[PDB]
Image (cartoon, helix red, strand yellow):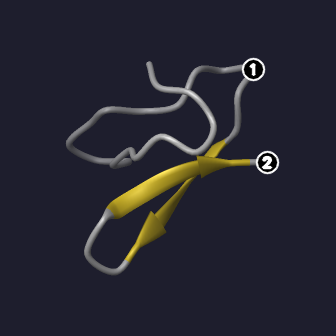
Amino acid sequence: CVLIGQRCDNDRGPRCCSGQGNCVPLPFLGGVCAV
């Protein structure tokens, strides 16, 4: 799992650590873990 400010992707991975943040999807960066 990845941490806040690190990029993630909800479907493909990676995904945020359960106590980190929600993986908010981003246009081209896939997503990012944010609170």
Residue at 53 percent of width and 31 percent of height: 16
Q: Earlier in the sequence, mark 1 or mark 2?
A: 1
Which residue corresponds to mark 2? 35
| Residue 24 position (above or below residue 33) | below
- Helix, strand or loop for disc 1: loop
The numbered dot on residue 1 is none
Q: Amino acid at mark 2?
A: Val
Q: Position of residue 26 (x, y in %)?
A: 42, 72
Residue at 63 percent of width and 37 percent of height: 4
Q: Amino acid at mark 1?
A: Gly
Residue 2 relative to residue 9: left or right: right
Q: Position of residue 2 (x, y in %)?
A: 47, 25
Quarter of the image holding residue 21? Answer: top right
Which residue corresponds to mark 1? 19
Residue in the foreground of this view, choosing between 9 and 5:
5
Residue 29 relative to residue 22: left or right: left
Residue at 58 percent of width and 21 percent of height: 17
Q: Position of residue 5 (x, y in %)?
A: 58, 45
Tag 1: Cα neighbours inside 10 Å, few (<14), some, or many (≥20)?
few
| Residue 7 position (above or below residue 19) | below
- Helix, strand or loop for disc 2: loop
Residue at 33 percent of width and 49 percent of height: 9
| Residue 3 position (above or below residue 13) | above
Tag 2: Cα neighbours inside 10 Å, few (<14), some, or many (≥20)?
few
Quarter of the image holding residue 30? Answer: bottom left
